[PDB]
Image (cartoon, coloured by chain):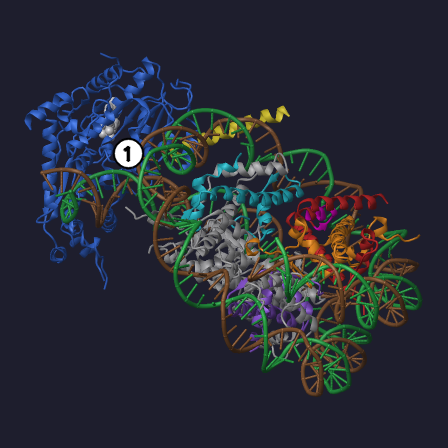
Chain colours: A yellow, B red, D orange, F blue, I purple, J cyan, K green, L brown
Amino acid sequence: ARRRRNLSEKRNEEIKMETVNKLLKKQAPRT
Amino acid sequence: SRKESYSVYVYKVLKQVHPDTGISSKAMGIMNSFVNDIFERIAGEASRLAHYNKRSTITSREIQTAVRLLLPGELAKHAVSEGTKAVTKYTSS
Amino acid sequence: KESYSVYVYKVLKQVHPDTGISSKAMGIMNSFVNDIFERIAGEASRLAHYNKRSTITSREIQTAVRLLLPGELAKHAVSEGTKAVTKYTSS
Amino acid sequence: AKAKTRSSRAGLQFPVGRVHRLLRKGNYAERVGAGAPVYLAAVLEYLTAEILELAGNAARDNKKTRIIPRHLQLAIRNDEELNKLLGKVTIAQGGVLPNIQAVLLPK
Amino acid sequence: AKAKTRSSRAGLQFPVGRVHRLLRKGNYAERVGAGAPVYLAAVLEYLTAEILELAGNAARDNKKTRIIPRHLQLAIRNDEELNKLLGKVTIAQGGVLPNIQAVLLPK
Amino acid sequence: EVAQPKLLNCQLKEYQLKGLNWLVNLYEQGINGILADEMGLGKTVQSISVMAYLAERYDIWGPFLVVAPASTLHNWQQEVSKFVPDFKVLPYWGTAADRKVLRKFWDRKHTTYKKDSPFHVMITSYQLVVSDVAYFQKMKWQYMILDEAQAIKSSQSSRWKCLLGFHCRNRLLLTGTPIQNNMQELWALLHFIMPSLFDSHDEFSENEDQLKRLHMILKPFMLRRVKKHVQKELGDKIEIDVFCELSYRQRAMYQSLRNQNLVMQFRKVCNHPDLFERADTVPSMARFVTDSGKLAKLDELLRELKEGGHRVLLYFQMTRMIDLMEEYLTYRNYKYCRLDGSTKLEDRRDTVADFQTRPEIFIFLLSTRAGGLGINLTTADTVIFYDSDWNPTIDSQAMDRAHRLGQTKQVTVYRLITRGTIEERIRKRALQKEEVQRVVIT
Amino acid sequence: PHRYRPGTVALREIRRYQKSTELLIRKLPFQRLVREIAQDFKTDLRFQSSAVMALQEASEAYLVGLFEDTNLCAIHAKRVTIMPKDIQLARRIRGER
Amino acid sequence: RYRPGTVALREIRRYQKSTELLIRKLPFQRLVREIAQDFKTDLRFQSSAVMALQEASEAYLVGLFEDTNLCAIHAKRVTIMPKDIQLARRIRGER
Amino acid sequence: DNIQGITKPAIRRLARRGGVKRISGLIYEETRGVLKVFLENVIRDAVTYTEHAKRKTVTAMDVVYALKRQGRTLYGFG
Amino acid sequence: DNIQGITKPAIRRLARRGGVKRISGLIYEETRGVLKVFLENVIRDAVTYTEHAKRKTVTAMDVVYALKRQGRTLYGFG
DNA sequence: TGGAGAATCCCGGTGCCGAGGCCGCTCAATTGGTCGTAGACAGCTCTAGCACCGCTTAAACGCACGTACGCGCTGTCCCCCGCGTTTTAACCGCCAAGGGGATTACTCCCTAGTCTCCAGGCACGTGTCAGATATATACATCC
DNA sequence: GGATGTATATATCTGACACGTGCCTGGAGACTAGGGAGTAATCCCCTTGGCGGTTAAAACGCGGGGGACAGCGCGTACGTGCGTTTAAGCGGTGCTAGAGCTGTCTACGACCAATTGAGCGGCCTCGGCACCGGGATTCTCCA
Ligand SMILES: Nc1ncnc2c1ncn2[C@@H]1O[C@H](COP(=O)(O)OP(=O)(O)O)[C@@H](O)[C@H]1O
């Protein structure tokens, strides 16, 4: 039980932080 | 030639509930009509239930959900009981 | 999962060439067509059964339209029906 | 080895075999479960009994030995649950439940 | 040999093959005519056209570019014959035809 | 009085340093205020320096809000990234699908941020501050700069009614033209600054003595400065009016209208006949150039400037006249760039960089209202205004885009006037209004 | 000499005809009407016997039900007499028009 | 302003022009979960299922009021009163 | 003609079975129009089933099926 | 006690869509009883389909079927 | 209350026809076997529904008030009920013609079935453009 | 001499559609089998029609009585508007139940052939019921 649920938070956090950063990179930095 | 009907079976049921009583041909015609009507409805309901679940077979469970949909109130309970009994006896035998 | 969306749009572009059709209104059209299919194929089904016959032909459809659609709508639909089956057979 | 009607095999007066035939020929679906006709037959017998019991009572209450349509009509409209099953049904030769509106009665 | 949709062979924006699949697999009968799906598809296309023609008109009378559920309701409940066909139907987000009894209006 | 902020990656000039001292004293007194430097003295780096000073002394590492017009947002993103590079700077612009994601930076629970926090400065448009006020109202903004603040001059605007209700401590206005129109608009800026003191339309209304009255009254709330006292190294604007006479086609249409509400229709004829109805029974490009007095006279002037190796900023008031002008520039085979309010906010960055990076480009076409604010165009040298604006502040704002700091050539302003027509009336009124504004500051 | 008061005879009638099963339209004129409607739709139509009996059971069942509904519309309007406006209300609420 | 009654008829010309749902969402939803849990405990609902029930529920009530209105007007009243609901139901066949 | 074969006395009776005490005078002509509009709809469907079967004879079954296409189900004839 | 959550204002708006000018005060308690009886009947059916499919969640489709079981066809949701 | 008296129910005797029982027999229901796919099952990903928290602000509520509808009561007068007599056509029991539906045989073409192949349509991206909201400015109008 | 409405611009944004790549599954073509529906010949039943007779009921004509209707007063309920209060609606964070999909394989129902008894048609028949004449009892009505 616990292991899969713990891993879900890390897997979520990674994608959330990257997709957050990608949007700031989308606007501020030239594309 | 050979038109076929449920009059035979209605007589037996009547004999178990009211031993001395009988039944005019017109009343029996009404009973024959009633039985076709209700088979129609319970089969049609069971048909559509199977379709909505994307299933190919009309099992006993479907005929159960259909009784529970068509019949109102206490009728439904008492019928779903007769059904369980019968199928239990068959599965035994 | 399939819908009749595509075809409704094609009919719309041909009858009203400037217009579009909202997502929810398209959902209403997909509901309408499924409904009427069921009604017509159900009447065809029963007509076959009442006549002890094992195939739903095109004659069974035409009698089921004459039973379902009210008044002048029926006449027009049976005309359209008959036209198309003629053209297909002519190929 | 000696035959036993599926009906007797399942304790029922209504004909299990014929019901399996009609479920197969009625295009209700492709494959028809075995117990399906047994259960369906049990419910048809139950409903048949329920009406005829009530009709028998109506006949005795009118001093006669044969059920006729008028007794079925009385039976069916005097029970709320059967009436909710058959509200749209007309019974030929049935007549009407006796009911005069109370404001029509004389002063 | 190059394949030509049944639709094209019969001039029918509606998909005659899909109609034949649904009639065949949906247990309406044991066997289906080759003429069945062509005729039925012609009738669906005709009714689809009728409702969209009336709704298209109602859109342009309201000075708007896009058909919405309000306009389908207004279309369907004006035509005598389509209203008779869809009398039981509720259309989501459709609202009511404007209607006041002349008894309610000012003297 | 105060030292330069240690985080600041550039040296402040003397008058900028004094400006920071004023603002620091305002913050420590708890008073809100207007930095009103004449355009291109460097309000931006002074503004930024307060965020630096707060982040150093009182360890208030944000959150800080810059609200600015659209043309200008990219400028701020660069400026903060350049002059205080430790600060972490978050755009709040772009589509709704973008902005949702950006809100996921905001910390609603820590009231004062510190260096490790997700973002320190947010930069957003006036337009999004209004549309997304529902979401902003939850924040606890620690310092807030409205740049190009005459955006808020109308008290009846949704914008004023929104920004007044932003929950925040210290506010700074920047506006290089504070005094604008009637005294009601001056009330509006004051109220946005300090609601309790300037609470009434009527009492602010409550003549030479009244003007002397005002000069003292404003002294605790505004710092105004002017180029000639500190930017002595850059020569004054050479301004050259040019007259034009209507073409025969213009003259016909103008008489037709005058014989036949028609204010804006007259302004169109004086720009170019083709802004009414174009041409073809075949229409020649030579007729197009000759058919408008302005364009005809402009053709002389452009050709001279090209031969001399100058580069031109050319302003319009009418957007369709930009469309027409590109055609004439295409035929004369001049390289040009275009920027107006319809231009997507990505392309703004690119275009301004292009004209400041690659001197093949001869002409920048700019809309006056979109072009007038923010953008920095030091590589240009000649400004042309093709049409007069009713409001003199807007043209002022516009020509100061050529006359910044770091300009090294003599800025030349041309202005074309169509004689005997609405154009004259308009420039007449604008100059009256400029005298009034100049008197009230003076 | 004797007359019953207006209404007593009618209530006699309600009891008697609410207690009989019999068909209330005369058979031969009903049968003749059904063929008059049929002959619009297809010419030379032989009718089974039980088909016209079934039409008559349905026809009497429809009208006897319509009078029940009509009567409630009258009583609600504080009348005892049914009038054409009552029938039209009942049909409209039941959706037939 | 408006003579006595013109305001009610303005209410009519308002609500017949709009298409919106007329019951408040969250109160409706709570009623549906109250009724449901008699039949089975722990019934999860889909958003779209509660919206379906609400569209159907409002459509039903509105249509009952048109039939109720006709009953009133037939009695030479403009006011709908409980007797009128009960009459419509019995005619329609909802006893 | 034939519709006037449904006599005034007949309607009066039908009404009594529906328990109506007092009957107007204009009811009679309205009732006839109602009954004809009902019969026309049922007969059209019954004749339509008859012609699909290529029979000439309208049977009891055609009528019974016609009525079940109207929500009115008749028990006691097929 | 959630049925009283259907507010008086709301019943009144529904009436107005139905073209009612003036409403009695007793209408409110009838209308609540009416609405609950209708929802009980549809929800019972929807849950009956849901349990047959061995789902725990009542879907839109269950409800749309439950209404076509009762002659009330809801176009707009699958 | 009291006779009157028309109607209703209950009693009883006749007789008739259809409910009910019993005889052959044919065809469909039962027994025992094969086999092939539906679907029960185990396991998985990940959608999305249930909880719970704070804020604006709209609709929900409560009250004081007044006037319009509902409705109880009366006078009028038409029109329906009740009854009587004449008139007519429905019903009955019957004979007959004959059409048309139900059946038996038999043949052929149509549709299901399997296989090979490829393009229509579904899902997901994206971008671009007309419509909706702000905001600025002059000027005419209403006060 | 001022407060506001109107008309025309620019500046922006948001959401509707047009097009796009991709991929995949179901529709199209083509080939054979065999059974359903189409053909005609037959046959007996049940419908259409005529006849003469009885008699139930429909058709017509009167009074007169009581109900539909129109009008009026009056009284209490319903609509209104002003002021306040409470929950709905928004939008979030965040957890995890359970919907929806995959891969197995087993067990069950379609399909066949041989059997045999259930249930249909038909024939005989006698007892439940309809109906009739009579008497006793119950409801209306008016003095
Ligand atoms: N120390 C400095 N180093 C570089 N640029 C500076 C410095 N001081 C001022 N500037 C210039 O100041 C300009 C900003 O002027 P400012 O008045 O703030 O802009 P705006 O008028 O748009 O508000 C920029 O072009 C910037 O390059």
The residue closer to the viewer here, D68 or D43, is D68
Relative to the observer, which residue lies in front, K63 or F375? K63
Ligand 1 positioned in quadrant: top left
**With A22 as the anchor, is F239 left or right in this view?**
left
**Vertical placement of B73 versus B44: above or below?**
above
**Most distant residue in the left direction:** F208
Q: Give the range drawn in magenta.
A: B56-66
Q: Where is residue I40 in the image (x, y as percent from the top left)?
A: 57, 70
Relative image position of residue F283 (x, y in whole percent): 22, 60
Q: Is residue F125 above or below residue K125?
A: above
Q: How crowded is mark 1: few (under 14 residues within 10 Å), some or many (20 or more)?
A: some
Q: What element carries label 1?
A: helix
Query: On what subunit does the disc labeled 1 rest?
Result: F
In the image shown, does F5 or D12 lie closer to the viewer? D12
Residue D22 shows in the view: yes
Tell me residue L63's x, y (percent).
Answer: 49, 71
Residue at the limit of the structure toward the top, as seen here:
F1
Which quadrant of the structure image shows residue F281? Answer: bottom left
Position above or below: F120 against F372: above
Was residue F358 drawn as part of the magenta stretch in this picture? Answer: no
Instruction: Tell me if residue F311 can be seen.
Output: no
Rendered image quadrant of residue L75: top left
The kind of residue on which mark 1 rests is Arg
